[PDB]
Length: 196
Length: 65
Length: 49
Image (tube, rainbow over all chains, first blue to last red; front, side, top):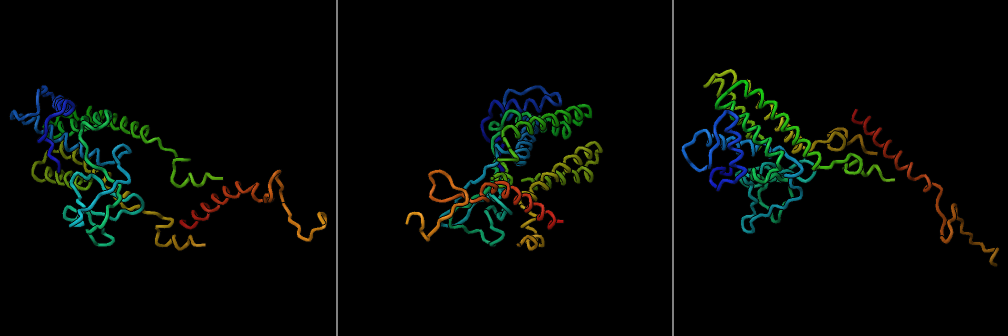
């Protein structure tokens, strides 16, 4: 699992943590560097948790289709990193699982590959790499969970519940606009049925 | 990753019920587990790739002409 | 003779400048494909049911 607190802070990550701190009324911090601020450290942990959770759900922008994972030539092992939020097959039923930190073919009962495998993969990205609407949803969900766990204010709980639903709605609008999905000619099955 | 979140969410909910006991935390974690299970159910279908026409054990035989 | 060749090539639907004729079915092959798609889906639905 990637360490959230071991790299330099970005401006957006500084903004996100302070937004989470604001949810319970904590004043903003100038830096995420260790100042013994338990609240800021807790907020960053929840920010990382929510960042991993929403990305792992799967969206057109972050789902990578047709990605090749190359094996080591001498060990024939493909690493299944903890930053692989989702690893699927390109079509049909998926055959690859995680076994000991390496890719395992459950149908062939083998973890040895002579060549790269093509998978539909979600790889963890920085919160800085998220779209603006997705950043807002991550912060809103992190703020809601932060208040529930470390303050518990029931009035704050209700408003952040509504804010997250609105934040998730606008992320769904982004995903549909980004996807540009068509059930007539963008459809795997129906587009073939349209040929005359 | 989705299953890890569901395990952690469900473990947190059971931990609160057993070793914290705050009822407002219970309602929060009940909501989170329901969402956490929903995303794992989405993962199961995407991984499963199940088809009732040709992937079906019985209907696939019925489709032969 | 030009007019009495025992080999008679027949064209169902003759187009200008074409050595061969078009079939009558190909004028409606589009509807046949569309009906084929519907009929396949209707039968396959019954097989699920």
